[PDB]
Image 1 (cartoon, rainbow, N blue to C red):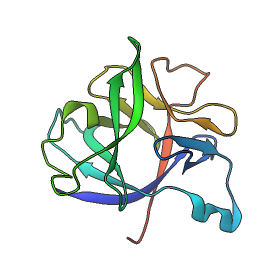
Image 2 (tube, rainbow, N blue to C red):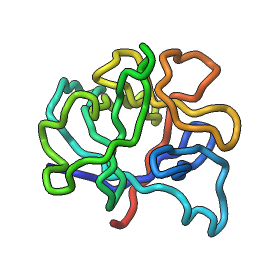
Image 3 (tube, rainbow, N blue to C red):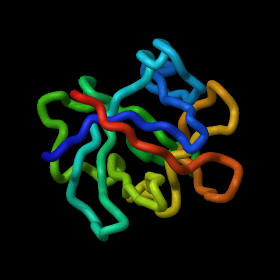
Image 4 (cartoon, helix red, strand yellow):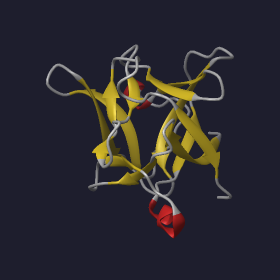
Length: 151
């Protein structure tokens, strides 16, 4: 399946890092300290495609860990999910693992295919978790830049 290596940064130049085994945190990084930032493998999976909307999966580079969208207390929730490392990645990923990547003026948004109008969001503050957020509108950050890495 076609994959790209990549880092994400939020519109405020917060970089993404592993908090626990299973959380991402967003934080202002610079210097050699930038080593500490998470590389994704972004996969081009089967789904609903327009010029503006591309379905992707987001895995970590050489881990069998994928971002999925899951119901946790009657709320859409973002987790890191362990997968069978022999079976993944796929062209037909399961719907929880699928994001619609939206280009909206040199910025990206990641909408969950599974919960419409839920987006990968970060906090305004340091050192808080990446979450699934349902409100675009000037409080949590929903847009990102993407950098390619020479993988």
